[PDB]
Amino acid sequence: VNSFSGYLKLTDNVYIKNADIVEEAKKVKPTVVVNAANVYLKHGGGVAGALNKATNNAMQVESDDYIATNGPLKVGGSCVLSGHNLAKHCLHVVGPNVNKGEDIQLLKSAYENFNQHEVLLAPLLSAGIFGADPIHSLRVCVDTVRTNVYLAVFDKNLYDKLVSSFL
Ligand SMILES: Cc1ncc(C)c(N)n1
C-alpha cells in the first residue's frame, strides 16, 4: 500500500492523475520525483522550472555543482540528486526535445531510467514544452516502465484525452 490518492489505474504498474507535480510532491513526499530535465540541468520552465521554483532555487544550485563536476547528461540519460523539500530524491531524466530536433526513439531510453526505482511520481517525458505527442509518451511509458509509476498530468483537457484514448 502507498500514499498516492485519486489516481486512475491504467495497467498493473502505471497510474495517472490530473495534478500539479509540485503540489502532489509536496503532499506525498515520495521517495522519487522525476524532473523533466535537459542535459545542462537548466531548470528554466515547464516541469523543471516549476519544481526548481518550489525548492527556492536549491535544485538549480545543486544542479550547477553537478554539471561543473560531471558535465552534461546524455539525451535519454538521468542522474539522481536531492529531492529537497519535495521528495527524498529527484531523478532528473532527459527526454528528447522535439523543438531541438532530437530522436524520439530516445524516449524509450529515457523511460528505462524509471526501472531503477521501485516507485516514482513523474510527468510524461518529452511532453509539454519538449514538443512530443503526450499520447505517444504515455504509450512508451506503459510499454517500457515495469516499476510502479504515478503520472501527474498538468492539463485537465489533456488528462481526459489521455484516459479516453488509452488502449
Ligand atoms: C505534471 C506537470 N507538468 C508541468 C508542470 C508545470 C507541472 N507543475 N506539472
Image (cartoon, grey):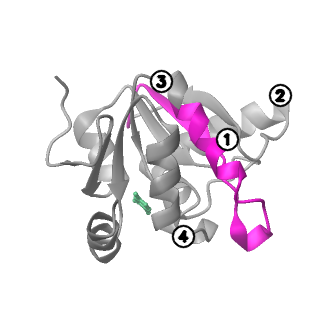
Tell me the number on the disc at residue 133.
Answer: 4
Q: Earlier in the sequence, mark 2 or mark 4?
A: 2
Q: Earlier in the sequence, mark 3 or mark 1?
A: 1
Q: Nearer the viewer, mark 3 or mark 4?
A: 4
Which residue position holds label 1?
A: 109
Q: Nearer the viewer, mark 3 or mark 2?
A: 3
In the image, what residue type sits under mark 1?
Ser
Q: Which residue is at 71% across, 44% downward? A: 76
Q: Residues within 10 Å of mark 2 (few under 14, many from 20)?
A: few
Task: Indicate yes or no: mark 2 CB to ligand 1 under 8 Å.
Answer: no
**Residue 1 image offset from top left, x and y in percent:** 16, 22
Q: Residues within 10 Å of mark 3 (few under 14, many from 20)?
A: some
Q: Disc 1 to disc 4, how far (Cα)?
A: 17 Å
Which residue position holds label 3?
A: 117
Image vertical order of residue 10 relative to residue 84, above or below:
below
In the image, what residue type sits under mark 3?
His
Q: Is residue 135 left or right of residue 93?
A: left
Q: Residues within 10 Å of mark 4 (few under 14, many from 20)?
A: some
Image vertical order of residue 37 relative to residue 116, above or below:
below
Q: Secondary structure at mark 1?
A: helix
Q: Nearer the viewer, mark 3 or mark 1?
A: 1
Which residue position holds label 2?
A: 69
Where residue 96 sits, quadrant-wise, is bottom right
Q: Are marks 1 and 2 in contact (CB under 8 Å)?
A: no
Q: Earlier in the sequence, mark 3 or mark 4?
A: 3
Q: Which residues are magenta?
A: 86-114
Residue pushed farthest bottom?
A: 157
Q: Which residue is at 47% across, 55% downward? A: 139
Q: Secondary structure at mark 3?
A: loop
Residue pushed farthest front?
A: 167
